[PDB]
Image: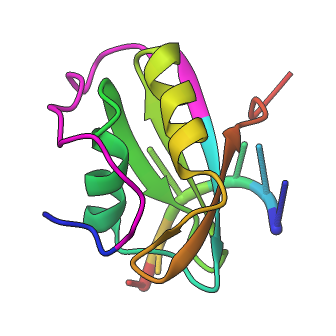
Amino acid sequence: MQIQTDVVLPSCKKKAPAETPVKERLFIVFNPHPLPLDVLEDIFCRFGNLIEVYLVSGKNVGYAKYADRISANDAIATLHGKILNGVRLKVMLADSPRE
DNA sequence: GACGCA
C-alpha cells in the first residue's frame, strides 16, 4: 500500500523465501513510537530480498532481515533519518546478537 | 537506541 511520506520509495518487491539465509540485518529506531508490522514490511520490502521485519515489544526498536547486502544498504541510504507515516526512522547495520 | 508479548 502507499506510504505517507515524501521520500521517493521503490515499488513493492516480493519477499525472499522464508528459509533464505540472512546476509544482512538492520537495526531500526522509531521516534516517537513503532510503526505497524504490516506497514514496516511494506516499507522494507521495496528494497528487494526482504526476509522479514520484526519488533521488540515494549521498546522503540525493530529489525529487518535481508537476503542481500545491496538491498539492505539501499534501505539504509533511502530511509535513515526520514519520516514515514509520521515516524522518524534511524536505520543502520545491526550489531550481531552474539560473539 | 539493542535483541522477537499478550
- Residue A20 highlighted magenta (yes or no): yes
Q: What is the quadrant of the C terminus of chain A in the image? A: top right
Position of residue A68 in the picture relative to residue A50 (left or right): right
x and y, in percent, of residue A14 in the image: 14, 31
Number of labels in the image equals 0
Residue A96 appears at what percent x and percent y? 76, 29
Residue at x 44%, y 27% (from the top left corner): A66
Q: Nearer the viewer, residue A76 or A94?
A: A76
Q: Which residue is at a point 28% across and 19% down the rendered structure image?
A: A19
Residue A27 in percent (x, y) is at: 65, 46
| Up-down relation of residue A34 to residue A81 (above or below) | below
The single residue placed furthest to the right in the displayed view is A99
- Magenta residues (range): A5-25
Could you tell whether A15 is left or right of A37 in the image? left
Residue A67 in percent (x, y) is at 40, 18
Residue A35 is left or right of residue A89, and the answer is left
Q: Which color mode does the image show?
A: rainbow
| Residue pictured at 53% horizontal, 51% vertical | A79
| A17 and A85: which is toward the camera | A85
Instruction: Specify the quadrant of the image occupied by residue B1.
Output: bottom right
Residue at image coords 57%, 84%: A33
* Quarter occupied by the N terminus of chain A: bottom left
Q: Most prominent secondary structure in the magenta stretch?
A: loop
Instruction: Choose between A49 and A7: the one closer to the eye.
Output: A7
Judge from the rendering whether residue A9 lies leftward or rightward of residue A79; answer left or right: left
